[PDB]
Image (cartoon, rainbow over all chains, first blue to last red; front, side):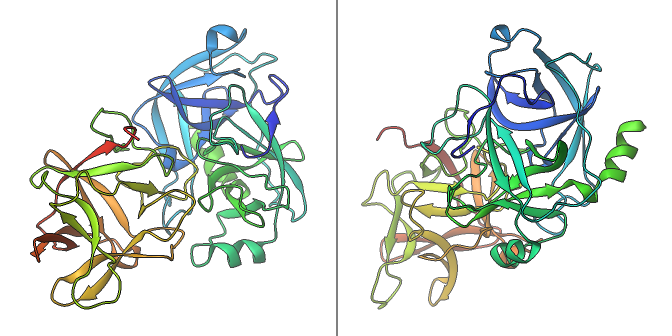
Length: 223
Length: 165
């Protein structure tokens, strides 16, 4: 997260850490006691998932759980066309007990509103090119579809939307993939991709447009 | 699924670190820039025996992940993350053929993938980001090996993190 700050601890109790040999590579979002939503490009044959974290050391985080998962379902249209439909559902080996620090979040049914100020959270790179010690939070504003398609031509697809690109250079960065974009208290997007390098002035990041996928998510998770 | 790893078994980073492409069968030669013929500037990518260990590259995906998989379309470039003047692309030039050359422009999504092959990895070029990839191999000329599309005859590399700097 570029030009954000420490989240208030456990203010984002749906946040999931995807770790591989004790290194974070992506985030996800608890959307059901037994399922984490993430970007399809974060796919792995198995996962270690941190719930209830703030720093990435579980033994310093009362209420935290490191859980295993082996099963993931990528959206059937992932990457058709390229970069589009970037979401997947990870089934935890065990359902998780709700607490004050571990809680699911609902997905927005309404599509994003241009001008809406939203929150993105993650453990990805900071402006200084280092990894943060604790979960970072930043506000970014939804941008119009017209600006989004102009900037990301010829790859723009309605499974995507843009947020950020303000003068204050707030953005998602490497390690933030799969993490949540919250608008009006609902899960609106997942960090997906953007221009390298991150934080360029006037360059918003691209988020998976989750309002387009609520039926697919509900049907996969209820099964 | 398939994470690209360096010679120490660590995941290759998305843009943040530079890496030497070390040929498994041409280890006496390193990546460098050269002219093909009479062009004004050296912009063809070659393995040159006179340059060791050669110019390190960065692999770049627009995806906000910090590692690289074999399924990702990549830009490959010389130089720092901040600069886009050493970005690889493919240009027809006789007598090499479809040669790998540096440009100062970059698409959001590059045309290369890094795929497992033998002891290491090959670079595969996908014209128009289609479904069909063409192996990058070597054309010997002027005491250098020009990187060029040579489908079925890939140059195989191992990927060595340039932390020595």
